[PDB]
Image: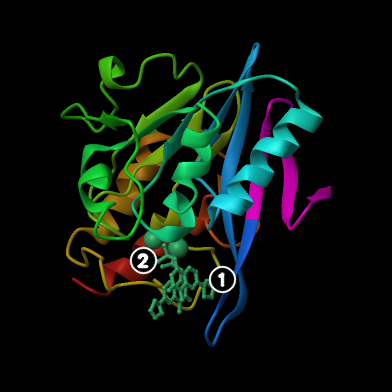
Amino acid sequence: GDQRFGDLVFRQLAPNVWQHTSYLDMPGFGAVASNGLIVRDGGRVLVVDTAWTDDQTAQILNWIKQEINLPVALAVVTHAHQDKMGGMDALHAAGIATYANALSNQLAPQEGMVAAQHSLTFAANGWVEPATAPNFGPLKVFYPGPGHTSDNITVGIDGTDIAFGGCLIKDSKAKSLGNLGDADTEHYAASARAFGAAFPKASMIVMSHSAPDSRAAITHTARMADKLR
Ligand SMILES: Cn1c(=O)cc(CP(=O)(O)O)c2ccc(N3CCCC3)cc21
Ligand SMILES: Cn1c(=O)cc(CP(=O)(O)O)c2ccc(N3CCCC3)cc21
Ligand SMILES: [Zn+2]
Ligand SMILES: [Zn+2]
């Protein structure tokens, strides 16, 4: 069920949830996938992560207009790297309210990214403070601790068995933890397990750069990360 639209792919995961996929040519790697989510909540649409670029992100909004034809209320981004935040200006151009971890907004300018308009803060138990994430509805946002990056956040969709760990979680067949340049190797394993414990009923774990996987993706990530302590 891959639906093509311009240079992006959309896959329905649940009645009100789609995966968006965009591609960037990376030296030595070919055309690399980056995934995010689109959630319909009543008369509005919510987006998790931008595409790699503004032009790709504008495509996501065009697909939404064509397939759903409801306004995009807000977008949240999972960390300050090009794959998840590279299209922030396309959301601003569209008048969409944007949210990121406060640390993601602090890091974004130096990473050559546009900061979100709103900063998220987190309770002691990792769950987003609702006063910083107003109107999020079925989007449940969780800071699991540092891993792929210090700012990485994760999201579950209430009324579904879907959770998304962004770049924190690797696929169950991965041979690498990937980008360790900005990673917290001492805390990585605990952060991966904290994500699994936050969404214990999630059976469909959306991957950052590959097709959806099982909870084995969380287990495999944490076991690889245990090796770096
Ligand atoms: C090279 N590179 C980069 O320079 C940057 C990314 C983005 P992030 O650090 O994963 O946020 C990247 C993402 C995926 C990726 N591939 C996945 C399968 C093979 C390589 C490469 C990436
Ligand atoms: C190899 N690899 C991979 O196999 C996978 C990733 C993506 P993730 O970090 O696991 O989400 C990846 C990301 C960045 C990267 N490098 C950036 C500079 C050189 C390579 C490599 C990655
Ligand atoms: Zn990243
Ligand atoms: Zn990644």
Q: Which residues are magenta?
A: 1-21
Is residue 212 something that shows in the picture? no
The answer to which quarter of the image holds residue 60 is top right
Mark 1 residue type: Lys
**Residue at the outermost bottom position:** 28
Q: Residues within 10 Å of mark 2 (few under 14, many from 20)?
A: some
Label ID, residue 173: 1
> What secondary structure do most residues of the magenta stretch adopt?
strand
Per the model, the C-alpha gap separating discs 2 and 1 is: 12 Å
Q: Position of residue 17 (x, y in %)?
A: 66, 32
**Image quarter of the C terminus:** bottom left
Residue 8 or 94: which is nearer the viewer? 94
Q: Is residue 13 above or below residue 68?
A: below
Residue plotted at (35% across, 47% down) = 114
Mark 2 residue type: Arg
Q: Position of residue 131 (x, y in %)?
A: 27, 15
Helix, strand or loop at mark 2: helix
5 with respect to 48 (left or right)? right
154 with respect to 132 (left or right)? right
Residue 25 or 176: which is nearer the viewer? 25
Residue plotted at (25% across, 65% down) = 183
Helix, strand or loop at mark 1: loop
Is residue 131 something that shows in the picture? yes
Residue 26 or 151: which is nearer the viewer? 26
Task: Confirm or deny contact between disc 2 and disc 1 (CB under 8 A).
Answer: no
Q: Position of residue 25 (x, y in %)?
A: 59, 75
Magenta stretch: includes residue 211: no
128 with respect to 46 (left or right)? left
Residue plotted at (50% across, 58% down) = 217
Residue with the mark numbered 2: 223
Q: Position of residue 129 (x, y in %)?
A: 25, 21
For ligand 2, the image quadrant comes to bottom left
